[PDB]
Image: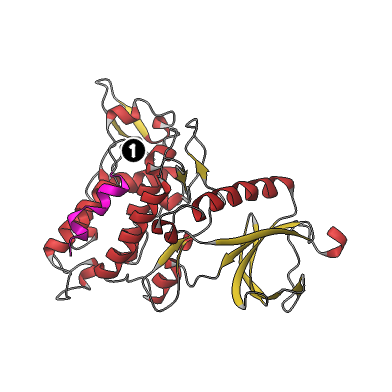
Amino acid sequence: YNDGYDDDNYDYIVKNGEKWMDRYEIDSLIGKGSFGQVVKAYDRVEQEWVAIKIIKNKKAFLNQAQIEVRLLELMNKHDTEMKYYIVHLKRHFMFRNHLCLVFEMLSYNLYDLLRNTNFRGVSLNLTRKFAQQMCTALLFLATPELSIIHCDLKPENILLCNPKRSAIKIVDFGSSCQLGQRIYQYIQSRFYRSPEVLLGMPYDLAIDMWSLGCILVEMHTGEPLFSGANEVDQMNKIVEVLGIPPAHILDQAPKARKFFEKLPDGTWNLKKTEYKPPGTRKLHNILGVETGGPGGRRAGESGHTVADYLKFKDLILRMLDYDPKTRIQPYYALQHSFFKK
């Protein structure tokens, strides 16, 4: 297997302490995925820690990573300070038949941060800081020259720069694409998957704003807003909160009948699979708008007022629009009264 460098998964066999090109000292494995592995390495030449993503020695993964390199170079080269919300690709090289992407070293992901709260959530003030940064990232990605859909926004793909600050970056553009001939594919992690993708409809940059709405509620409550066991359970959990999607969406949706029934009058209802009736699990109640925030845990805390929670709820409801056309766009998210401080 690759002169004994590769296992039967086409992954490089990582050896702690190995030195590459008389430059990089591999410290440890920090990550693993379909793509391959991520290692922590000390770059002797630049005198700094780096994260090296070691792509599997297999053509399809190498070709996908060449797309990831192309998008990262597009973003990293833009002449705006908004690009600092995206992880920096320092360089890439071919080493022992593996494509290696060399990234800046970031810190814990937002899932680690949730685990650190014991899944009770961070304050509304810290939620606001994360929301403002992510909306600015999505504003950047939707620049016409870029038109990048991340396609896998989730707490695990949002990393703190460092353990002390609220500064964050988006990582893992390995599944990302540029807006093009709009096509359906089975994409996004299920809990964060937009209704258009669940419904088998073609997708655009709005799927990232849906994922963001879900992420922001989770960051405050400590738990996923829509934790589906499968796609039917996922859509049923979305309907518990948001009600039956508009008829004009379901009338155009190839998978409408996986989840919904069209009745003789042209109206739609849930298919029989249990669940709260449609719209009974209000975001008003999930956030504890009038009852001291999630599980009443923010009762008499600064910047956790009914007015604050009403502004948060209104922003999330605009991010969780069933219609990708009227779903709030990043610029207007940033002008929302939730950010007026």
Pick out the residue farthest to the top.
264
Picture residue at 40% right of the left edge, 59% below the top = 81
Pick out the residue farthest to the front.
79
Using residue 326 as the reference point, say whether residue 134 is left or right of it: right
Picture residue at 47% right of the left edge, 37% below the top = 179
Q: Which residue type does callout 1 highlight?
A: Pro
**Picture coordinates of residue 248, whole percent (x, y):** 29, 27
Instruction: Please tell me in which quadrant of the rendered image residue 136 appears.
Output: bottom left
Using residue 97 as the reference point, say whether residue 325 is left or right of it: left
Range of the magenta residues? 328-341
Residue 4 at least partly seen: yes
The residue to which callout 1 is attached is 324
Picture residue at 27% right of the left edge, 64% below the top = 128
Using residue 91 as the reference point, say whether residue 7 is left or right of it: right
Q: Say which quadrant the N terminus sits in.
A: bottom right
**Picture coordinates of residue 198, whole percent (x, y):** 43, 40
**Picture coordinates of residue 261, whole percent (x, y):** 34, 29
* Colouring convention used in this rendered image of the protein: secondary structure
Does the magenta segment cover residue 332?
A: yes
Q: Please, what secondary structure does the residue beneath circle 1 have?
A: loop
Looking at the picture, does residue 141 appear above or below residue 1? above
Residue 100 at least partly seen: no
Using residue 171 as the reference point, say whether residue 82 is left or right of it: left
Looking at the picture, does residue 328 appear above or below residue 87? above
Instruction: Please tell me in which quadrant of the rendered image residue 115 appears.
Output: bottom left
Pick out the residue farthest to the right.
3
Picture residue at 41% right of the left edge, 72% below the top = 113
Q: Say which quadrant the C terminus sits in.
A: bottom left
